[PDB]
Image: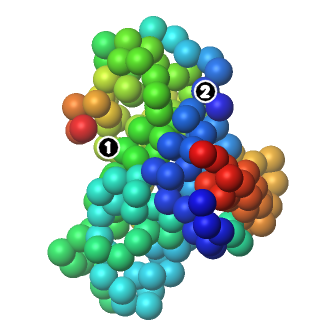
């Protein structure tokens, strides 16, 4: 392997040969939504997350979506959030048998149910309309919500460092 | 890290997400 500054979530899963943990799921969600919110503000077009290969985790803890007011366009925020929600659940389910299901903490399960529009605060949360809505739910996972920006960067920084050693050195 | 798993429920989140592929 050769050392670089980003790995895809697909590569991360392949290297681990196991699913991501719950804290990593919250972190990728928060960090990727932050990147997407900023990209939209700078008028880069929205597009959907088609697969885990498109999600890039960086050395400094950033998470971005690789390339292919603006409130309405050919790709709405909720569509991007849905596609991200589905990919995050696949990452949490990675390698499990079809007849097994992971027992997620209720607030993480709820976040994902609402991201993915699979819903059929203790019963149901307000519908997610924006990247900021998702980020606020991830911040709420923490006892002190103002810790979120630093915390979720630190989570992805560690995930990168840990998998980069497998990337560089696994044969 | 997966650790804790249950049997797949017929109406649960895994069930619903699988049908969106």
Image position of A36 with respect to B7: above or below: below
**Side of A96 relative to A47 (left or right):** right
Q: Are marks 2 and 1 on the same chain?
A: no
Q: Whole-percent x and y of residue B13?
A: 39, 27
The 10 Å Cα crowd at callout 2, few under 14, some 14 to 19, many 20 or more, is some
Q: Chain of mark 2?
A: B
Quarter of the rendering containing residue A113: top left
Q: Which mark is residue B2?
A: 2
Judge left or right: residue A139 versus residue B9.
right
Residue under the point 48% across and 75% down: A37
Mark number for residue A117? 1
Q: Quadrant of residue A30?
A: bottom right
Q: Position of residue A102 (x, y in %)?
A: 52, 22
Residue lying at 43% horizontally and 68% vertically, measured from the top left: A65
Say which element carries label 2.
loop
User: Which quadrant of the figure contains the N terminus of chain A?
Assistant: bottom right
Give the camera-side residue of A47 and A106.
Answer: A47
Residue A100 in sight here: yes
Mark 2–mark 1 distance (CA, rounded to whole Å) = 24 Å
**Furthest residue toward front:** A171
Residue at 40% from the left image edge and 47% from the top image edge = A87
């Amino acid at each position: 392997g050769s050392s670089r500054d980003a790995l895809s979530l697909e590569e991360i899963l392949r290297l681990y040969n196991q699913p991501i943990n719950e804290e990593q799921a919250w972190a990728v969600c928060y960090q990727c939504c932050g990147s997407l919110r900023a990209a939209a503000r700078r008028r880069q077009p929205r597009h959907r997350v088609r697969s885990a290969a498109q999600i890039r985790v960086w050395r400094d803890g950033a998470v971005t979506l690789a390339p292919a007011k603006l409130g309405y366009s050919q790709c709405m925020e909720t569509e991007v959030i849905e596609s991200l929600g589905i990919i995050i659940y696949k990452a949490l389910d990675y390698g499990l048998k079809e007849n097994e299901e992971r027992e997620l903490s209720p607030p993480l399960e709820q976040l994902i149910d609402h991201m993915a529009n699979t819903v059929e605060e203790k019963r149901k949360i307000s519908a997610i309309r924006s990247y900021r809505d998702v980020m606020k739910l991830c911040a709420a996972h923490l006892p002190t919500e103002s810790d979120a920006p630093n915390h979720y960067q630190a989570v992805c920084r560690a995930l990168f460092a840990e998998t980069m050693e497998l990337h560089t050195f696994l044969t | 890290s997966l650790y804790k798993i249950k049997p797949r429920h017929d109406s649960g989140i895994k069930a619903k997400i699988s049908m969106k592929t």
